[PDB]
Image (cartoon, coloured by chain):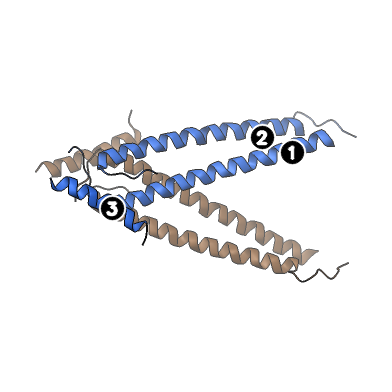
Chain colours: A blue, B brown
């Protein structure tokens, strides 16, 4: 009972160390921040999941195009053009997501070290 | 530059003034404000998605009243399954709603352990 326990070990170990330095935040914070940190990484993974899933739809669309009169279409974009810029968007988004998760990991490492206890992964 | 960097500063300087005369290191307040702001944003995007799906559903119900039929096996009709689409959605919206209450509490608690504002 359960991960509550490993938090405790984390806490007890630092309490021992503090009873004997650097930046230290109150030990009551460690479970609250480990939870927070964990929500945040989860939220990122689910964004990464979605972009993957949407990239997979895109691939399927390209498969359809290649498989399957035409008209004029105006001053707009063809469906093929629409798909190519779908991919572009998706790939920029996936880059955005990748840096966001590096930024977030850094932030959490900074928080750890200001706090004086572990929290990441 | 300026922007929210300034506001954080006023938050920090103010508390530094009180501390000079539970405490977390003041350098934490900007990192924690960012973090907290992310979490509420992530939450809101979820509330949005679920709203958007409850809207898709309302649309299905409408299409159903508008518009031949076989035996269908030992399963659920189109209207049966839409009705359960709505049930799931309503539950998700409820879990989403409690989650954001729990999350606010956590941040207030964090605030109080830290000794500075964050929401």
Residue B90 position within the rendered picture, expressed as x and y whole percent measured from the top left: 56, 64
- Measured Cα–Cα span from mark 3 to mark 1: 51 Å
Residue sticking out furthest to the right:
A69
Q: Residue at x 46, y 51 (%)?
A: B43
The total of numbered circles placed on residues is 3
Q: In the shown orientation, is residue A51 left or right of residue B78?
A: left
Q: Which mark is residue B97?
A: none
**Marks 3 and 2 belong to one chain:** yes
- Per the image, the residue denoted by label 1 is A61
Q: Are marks 3 and 1 in contact (CB under 8 Å)?
A: no
Residue A22 position within the rendered picture, expressed as x and y whole percent measured from the top left: 19, 37
Q: Which badge, 3 or 1, is on the more N-terminal residue?
A: 3
- Measured Cα–Cα span from mark 3 to mark 2: 48 Å
**Marks 1 and 2 belong to one chain:** yes
- Per the image, the residue denoted by label 2 is A86
Q: Which mark is residue A9?
A: 3
Q: Chain of mark 3?
A: A
């Amino acid at each position: 009972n359960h991960t509550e326990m490993e938090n405790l070990r984390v806490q007890l170990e630092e309490a021992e160390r503090r009873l004997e330095n650097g930046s230290q935040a109150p030990l009551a914070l460690q479970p609250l921040l480990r939870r927070t940190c964990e929500n945040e990484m989860a939220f990122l993974e689910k964004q990464r999941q979605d972009c993957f899933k949407e990239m997979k739809e895109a691939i399927e669309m390209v498969d359809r195009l290649q498989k399957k009169s035409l008209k004029l279409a105006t001053g707009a974009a063809s469906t093929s053009d629409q798909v190519d810029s779908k991919i572009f968007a998706l790939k920029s988004r996936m880059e955005k997501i990748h840096t966001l998760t590096r930024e977030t990991q850094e932030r959490w490492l900074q928080i750890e070290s200001l706090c004086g206890f572990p929290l990441l992964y």
